[PDB]
Length: 390
Ligand SMILES: Nc1ncnc2c1nc(Br)n2[C@@H]1O[C@H](CO)[C@@H](O)[C@H]1O
Ligand SMILES: [Mg+2]
Image 1: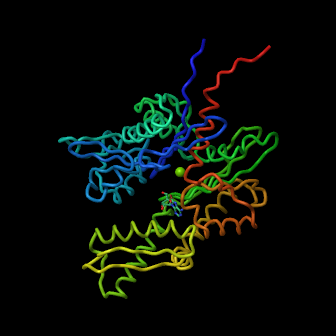
Image 2: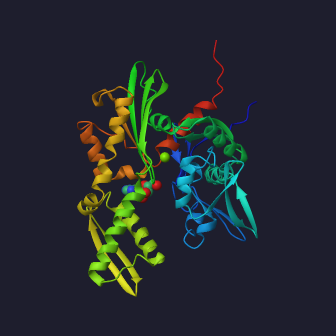
């Protein structure tokens, strides 16, 4: 009579990393890609012979900086003249050009100079997320829910839909990232009455705080606040500056002018930073870092916490601003939800918990996966077509 329907997917299309999930058998499965990664870099690289997307693109970025595109989400639905775009362009090694006051990324690809709209680069990331899901399900996927930041305007939301259509996806709905994180915890399924939820999202490059009110499963965004210049990369920069100084003291050598040595140092720092989230100390072991000198050292969690102390404390300023804008007191918040890999930092958790007088934080769903988790829950609800009984 009626053939079984393919599962719909939930995609968190992130600035730095993207994540895909599917709700099946009453639960969400976050789908690992072919390299065993549960998140995929939102990177696209172009060469004379190939277009590489995800881990393959991010792994060759060092020697191909001009033709490896990342951060397309910072350009999507914006005008070339927009002050945000103009400032961001100084930090990017790839070219951003002006086509009718719309930004386009220009690269060398398959023997030619090619320019792409931000939605086209995002469609390439969505194509990879769709293939990751089809590799797991074993059949073609058509339907998806895609998430966006709560502050995205109409043009930014329509360009995200356009990226989905280019990728061959039927976009069921564009939903806000803080709403998707709330849905992941079933915070819209608690019945009658108003609930105030604070979502604390600390990413690779930006920090966002959102206050939502939920009444009978209906979501209302009450306040948004954040810091565009606060993220995981700033903590990596503090460790980099620390070890450059340490090398200078120990071997009387300044490494800061050899890009490879700085890159190898930064790569090792980011991994030590992750180790320090579950360990009280971490080893740093780099062979022939500079002038054939082996750099074998360590860092305690206490020293790392001291190095980033001002940055961690500054996450509380947008929390207080969001609470003032929502016209609420901290005691009136019912649920605290953590989003982003940088929220695994014990000191970040301790500061926020202390601010809310020892309250529990919802962190049981991996914070780098919560948004895709909620998007997958919503995607399964949106494709239901039940006919009422008599
Ligand atoms: N366990 C973790 N402890 C500390 N930081 C982490 C962890 N896992 C992830 Br993922 N990160 C950081 O989150 C950001 C995501 O773009 C990057 O800066 C990652 O370094
Ligand atoms: Mg995110």
